[PDB]
Image (tube, rainbow, N blue to C red; front, side, top):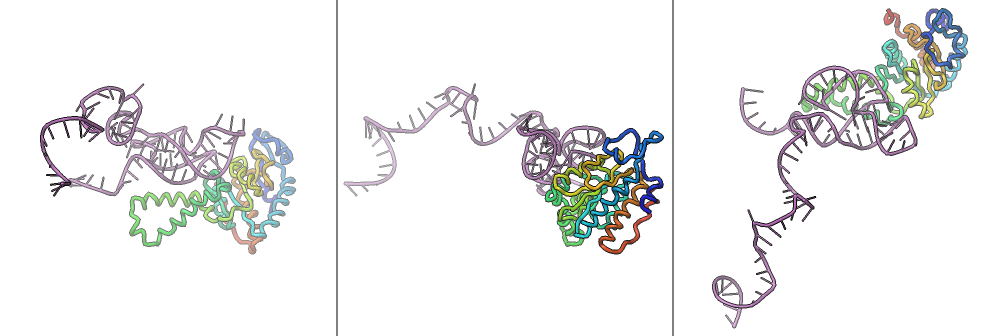
Length: 234
RNA sequence: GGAGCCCUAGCACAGGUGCUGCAUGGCCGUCGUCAGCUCGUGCCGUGAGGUGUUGGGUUAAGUCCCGCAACGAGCGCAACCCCCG
């Protein structure tokens, strides 16, 4: 089930590379590797979810990041089925602070979505049409998952604040609550709602997301079927 | 008697390739057709400021890509002009 399944092979993050605030989240250093306790998970996986249900109902919004490939393609699908924004490829500065300013790149799509139907293809000639294609392509690609926010979020969900603190400290200046999955390499002082564990365990990912999104759907109504991401493993 | 025009006398005068391009306006060359010059928002710094323009690669090129606390734009490259296929 929860930790029952998790208790399988989905913990323990690296070895002799850590930031000594995970002291209250580590069982033992047995056999060289560092191992994260799971009694504390439940004692921390609750309060997290518990106060999502205080926020998931009142129309709050959530952000999913994942500039690590072994989570990039996962956040992807698990974000649409969630219906909440996401930044799969790579995050870049300002998104939450320069919300107005980043949006012009998104609004651009509106002034670019006019084209692919409207009678200016016959007007707008090719040499800039062609070389704007990839521009439109790479504009959508890096920004799909942000093309659906004009209101600024109500949360942040991060696979690894060590990898994505750059997208956290932005939220931190906005007094916007920040949640994140944390590993032995993390820094569990800046995260508001802690979800410790191995973030680079490809396995310890897919199950985290549905179980995270299951609350999203259950907040909205009618849990469904996710995606058997096991094929994305080996 | 008067307007214009002409010559002769007094004028106000103009006139000078005389001087200073180290006093200037305008115009011209060099770097150089080099590829650089900057702004709005954001971030780092007490602050001047930095980032953006830096790193790898590519091209005639700040041309473009990856990454990057940055994302976009303006002047410039280009292209809109002309001759040839």
